[PDB]
Image 1 (cartoon, helix red, strand yellow):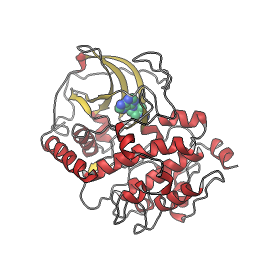
Image 2 (cartoon, chains in turn orange, green):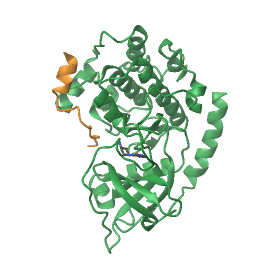
Image 3 (tube, chains in turn red, orange):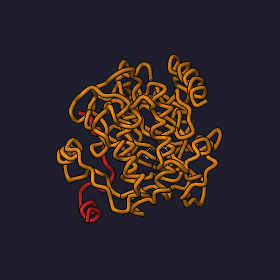
Image 4 (spheres, protein in one colour):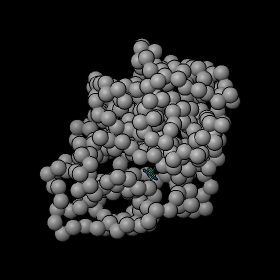
Length: 20
Length: 337
Ligand SMILES: NC1CCN(c2ncnc3[nH]cnc23)CC1
């Protein structure tokens, strides 16, 4: 499931801004 | 009208924009309590103002760290804009000041914690729950955009819940007053419009795309474009192709197809009818916009408080000293702060 793929991903915690 | 309200709002904003408040407190006037969030060159603490006993959120930036990250102008933007705005879903500056080492911005404290925390914990929000929040973002963007301000960092991490379960849109590190078009690569990977990724000039329309991502993530519990690495996420974003959960209602899907629209000539918020294409969409049909602005609407979730200055709705971060050099750092860079 997409839910399961999300939860297994490295990007469920707080996400940092990008900048260059 | 709306138009009338905004006309006056602009008048109020421009006076402060053109003559910014500067040096309106000192660190020794606050008692620091807890770190509420952290950042690259910055962090936000709960503080108590001793004279009044009021609690505030104090954003502390290390000037040297700002300079290393090439965020001098962006930081000046944040402070200049936040001291000038006033809107029920924004936290304007109450005070700002600087010392030898740091810049300080003092704002209303939202005790309910980040949307991020509650969304992740609960998993997803119901469409009415999602709509309650969306509406306040819609109104805030209408306000900011009418001031020629682009926000550029919509995500749940930046959406703070207050004691009444309403939202504060916080963190203006990338917010900018710009007429016409701009080029900086900034934001958060999951929320970037394809324009940004393809290094085109872009405008306020990227905030309406980020709104589409937010509403998707609130309603699904995960973003429309995700992967383990930013590159893979950018591939998905520019591909086109958004899949919606089966539980997404008909109206929701239609709203999202129109926000998450790569073609600028068709992306809602960006057309001839402006924000009203969003406001008058069927997904928002039960939204009383005046009552959202007025905060007369009943929040679908209301934070569990057990005191003022209680911080149970926040994660715990290691507490770092607020050190102050005996030498002034970066004085010229931050002269107008
Ligand atoms: N996600 C971060 C959490 C800590 N922050 C914060 N927290 C609480 N009240 C506030 N008022 C302005 N900013 C804040 C900033 C955003």
